Image (spheres, grey):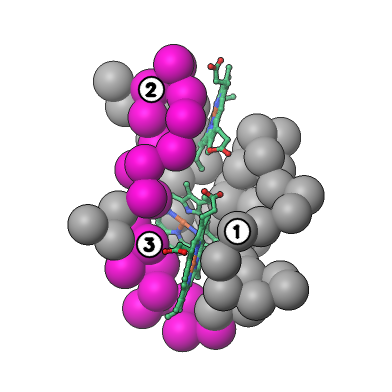
Amino acid sequence: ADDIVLKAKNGDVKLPHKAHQKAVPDCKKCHEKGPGKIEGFGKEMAHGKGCKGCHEEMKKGPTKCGECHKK
Ligand code: HEM
Ligand code: HEM
Ligand code: HEM
């Protein structure tokens, strides 16, 4: 499903793409060059300007280790 499970032996990080596709009608802040693969993103990113950045910037998403990584 939309859910785009990433890689992380520390606990997959189910990213409600769909939900995120609704909460962030602007498929740009997440998609640079455009909708699809992203060049630059990674781990640190998610832990910052990528997933958390918005989470900590917006204060809606998960912003804790036990708020993303869920075995
Ligand atoms: C907004 C409605 C929106 C669309 C449309 C969209 C499309 C899209 C595509 C086509 C892909 C590639 C997968 C494929 O080729 O089938 C993709 C992948 C990712 N997206 Fe996205 N996306 C939309 C919105 C958003 C938003 C708002 C975010 C972030 C909050 C986001 C994130 C991602 C991520 C991450 C991926 C895969 C890259 C990865 O790191 O694994 N999308 N999306
Ligand atoms: C980056 C790949 C990324 C991940 C991973 C991620 C995860 C995530 C989860 C698991 C939730 C929980 C919400 C739920 O009920 O499923 C969540 C919530 C929100 N996030 Fe997020 N998120 C990633 C990226 C981004 C980015 C880049 C933004 C903003 C640009 C963003 C925002 C939000 C919002 C908003 C929510 C909560 C919904 C709302 O209050 O509207 N996420 N995220
Ligand atoms: C909290 C401070 C926190 C820690 C610590 C942490 C650790 C961590 C590790 C060690 C990895 C690498 C995976 C491995 O070792 O195999 C990793 C990767 C990702 N994480 Fe994380 N993580 C912490 C918090 C968060 C939060 C709150 C989120 C979601 C907003 C998150 C997400 C991710 C993602 C995504 C990855 C992998 C990168 C990718 O491209 O998917 N982390 N984290």
**Placement of the N terminus among the 4 image quadrants:** bottom left
Q: CA distance from mark 1 to mark 2?
A: 22 Å
Is residue 28 placed above or below 63 in the rendered structure?
below
Observer-nearest residue: 62 or 1? Answer: 1
Q: Please rate how many residues cluster around mark 2, counting C-alpha atoms within 10 Å: few if below 14, some from 14 to 19, many from 20.
A: some
Residue farthest along the right direction in this orientation = 40
Q: Which residue is mark 3?
A: 17
Which secondary structure class fits the magenta region best? Answer: loop
> Could you say where residue 25 lies in the image, as x and y percent from the top left?
46, 84
The single residue placed furthest to the bottom in the displayed view is: 25
Question: Comparing marks 1 and 2, which lies closer to the viewer?
Answer: 1
The tag earlier along the polypeptide, 3 or 2, is 2
Q: Is residue 9 left or right of residue 18?
A: right
Using the image, determine if residue 64 lies above or below residue 37: above
Q: CA distance from mark 3 to mark 2?
A: 18 Å
Give how far across and how far down residue 56 sits, in percent: 60, 52
Q: Kindly indicate the quadrant of the structure image that contains residue 31.
A: bottom right
Amino acid type at circle 1 is Lys
Name the element at disc 3.
Answer: helix
